[PDB]
Amino acid sequence: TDQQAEARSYLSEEMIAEFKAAFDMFDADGGGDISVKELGTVMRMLGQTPTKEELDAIIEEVDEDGSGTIDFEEFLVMMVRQMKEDAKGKSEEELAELFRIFDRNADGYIDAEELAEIFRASGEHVTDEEIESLMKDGDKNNDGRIDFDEFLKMMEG
Ligand SMILES: [Ca+2]
Ligand SMILES: [Ca+2]
Ligand SMILES: [Ca+2]
Ligand SMILES: [Ca+2]
Ligand SMILES: [Ca+2]
Ligand SMILES: [Ca+2]
Ligand SMILES: [Ca+2]
Image (cartoon, rainbow, N blue to C red; front, top):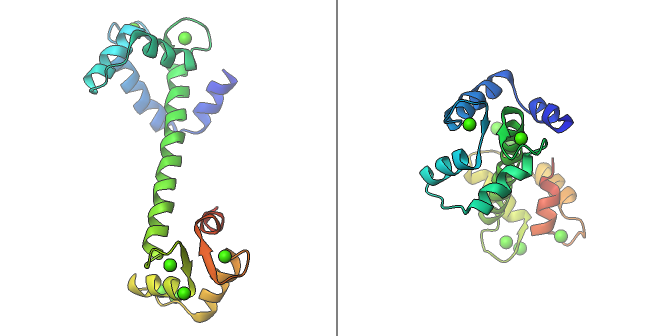
């Protein structure tokens, strides 16, 4: 429940209303909570084949009142945990892909020449001062190269 108030804070009124419409769809008998059987129906329609224990595990994750079912507030907690997981996955994909694009010769690090080339190719004029500054900040051991960990660190924020 303080967790439920916390979940609601990550969302706008409109997002909560969309989740409410989804919640009601899943709640096949319209009683106010999603059961293991109701969860299973939606999962099977999504192509999954969870076992009864796996369905039970999913509900238990957020079942704060021990009802063995997911009410709307618990559902919001589940949705927010998932949105957070998805956001983190999207960021990791973007970071890896960005590195993949900058490291043109695939030697494991980005050097000044590669930085400059990707910006130019992207249609952006970047000054030498700017490249210098980027290298100063990203390159922590000062060897003129930004390896994957430095890149991650320099991308934080
Ligand atoms: Ca129900
Ligand atoms: Ca519950
Ligand atoms: Ca390289
Ligand atoms: Ca080089
Ligand atoms: Ca510009
Ligand atoms: Ca510029
Ligand atoms: Ca370095």
